[PDB]
Amino acid sequence: ETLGEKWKARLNQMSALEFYSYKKSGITEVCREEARRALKDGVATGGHAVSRGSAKLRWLVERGYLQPYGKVIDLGCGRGGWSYYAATIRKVQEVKGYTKGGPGHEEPVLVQSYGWNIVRLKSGVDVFHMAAEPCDTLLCDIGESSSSPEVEEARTLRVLSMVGDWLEKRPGAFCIKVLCPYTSTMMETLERLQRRYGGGLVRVPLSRNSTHEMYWVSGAKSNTIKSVSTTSQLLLGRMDGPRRPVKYEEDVNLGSGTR
Ligand SMILES: C[n+]1cn([C@@H]2O[C@H](COP(=O)(O)OP(=O)(O)OP(=O)(O)OC[C@H]3O[C@@H](n4cnc5c(N)ncnc54)[C@H](O)[C@@H]3O)[C@@H](O)[C@H]2O)c2nc(N)[nH]c(=O)c21
Ligand SMILES: C[S@@+](CC[C@H](N)C(=O)[O-])C[C@H]1O[C@@H](n2cnc3c(N)ncnc32)[C@H](O)[C@@H]1O
């Protein structure tokens, strides 16, 4: 049993109150409420992000873990946070997002942030039932949580299988959600994939403690085992002391206009 698995076990064993305190203990959070007021008022200007995702991707870019450029594919784009953020980057020329939509799933949001005209979000698409196509930047944020670490592992594995085909067209720059990187098989498969395609795992502090999600990005390079175990150490450590205050931040502004 690995540290992450012990973390998952401890997590599931927690009482609901303890879990409420723990999920956001000491994490970085972005203020979103003005963005929700504006978005539900139908304000397409003002440069509001459609989701929290834009803050995540930003965190990865501003620290040089990936450098988006050219044609960007966003698998599981959802509302389009990653896509709309990617549209604001200089070297990025075109952004194409794909999401499942329908019952239980997010629909694409139309907004006129900077570079909205080079963005196209397609809904009603199963990326698993979709032929891969060439791209400079490969983004993927698929990985639904589960109380069962085995289910999370299986879903993550299916995701990696799916993104293999896109990666063999060889970008470039990529960022891929790894929901469950804390099992033995997962870490070994990630070692393999890291030797084949490069890149490394990175924990984003905007992530909640209730998820062990890490991001496989091209501009990172690190021992998978060590970074995963470091993350696990952080999450484990945050279960013992008092509740650490939330570090609130300003949400990313994506401006307005076309390109
Ligand atoms: C609500 N919840 C979630 N988790 C754990 O957190 C992980 C990720 O959770 P999340 O990041 O999706 O966000 P959160 O759960 O806070 O809210 P959301 O609505 O997004 O998640 C709902 C999911 O939580 C899970 N869940 C609900 N109640 C419990 C519970 N009593 N024990 C374990 N898992 C639960 C269900 O699978 C459900 O699909 C889950 O895989 C689960 O093991 C919990 N653990 C305890 N001990 N008590 C909880 O109440 C709890
Ligand atoms: C939570 S989102 C990511 C957030 C998004 N990047 C943003 O910044 O707004 C992940 C999305 O992937 C979508 N998804 C899950 N499985 C999918 C599949 N098989 N095909 C297409 N989209 C899927 C879900 O609907 C979900 O909205």
Image (spheres, helix red, strand yellow):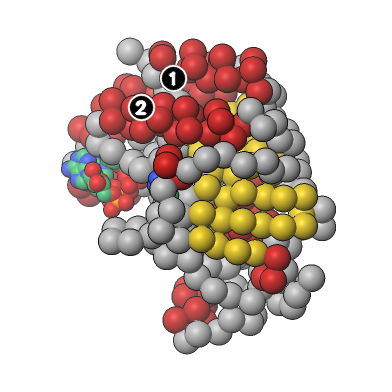
Answer with left or right where residue 176 lies relative to residue 245: right
111 over 139 or under it: above or below: below
In which quadrant is the C terminus drawn?
Answer: bottom right
> Can the viewer see residue 21 in this picture?
yes
Q: Which residue is mark 2?
A: 153
Disc 1 Cβ-to-ligand 1 distance below 8 Å: no
The residue closer to the viewer here, 113 or 206, is: 113
Task: Categorize mark 1 by other alpha carbons within 10 Å: few (<14), some (14-19), many (20+).
Answer: some
The label on residue 119 is none
Examine the rendered structure and indicate whether residue 94 appears above or below residue 3: below
Residue drawn at (75%, 75%) of the image? 258
Badge 2, how many Cα within 10 Å: few under 14, some, many 20+?
Answer: many
Residue 173 in the image, given as x and y percentages of width and height: 71, 38
In the rendered image, residue 85, in percent from the top left (x then y), is placed at 65, 60
Give the position of the N terminus as an image quadrant: top left
The quadrant where residue 154 appears: top left
| Label 2: which secondary element | helix
Q: Nearer the viewer, residue 53 or 32?
A: 53
Residue at (67, 41) in percent of width and height: 134
Instruction: Provide residue 200's location: percent of width, then percent of height.
Output: 63, 27
Contact check, label 2 and label 1, Cβ < 8 Å: yes
The answer to whether the beta carbon of the residue marked 2 is less than 8 Å from any atom of ligand 1 is no
Q: Residue under label 1, please give it.
A: 186
Look at the picture and state if 44 lies above or below 142. Answer: below
Residue visible at 50% across and 85% down in the picture: 42
Q: Residue at x 61, y 56 (%)?
A: 96
Front residue of 211 and 78:
78
Amino acid type of disc 1?
Met
Q: With 118 as the anchor, is 187 left or right in this view?
A: left
Measured in 3D between alpha carbons, the distance from the residue under mark 2 to the one under mark 1, in whole angstroms, is 7 Å
Secondary structure category for the residue under label 1: helix
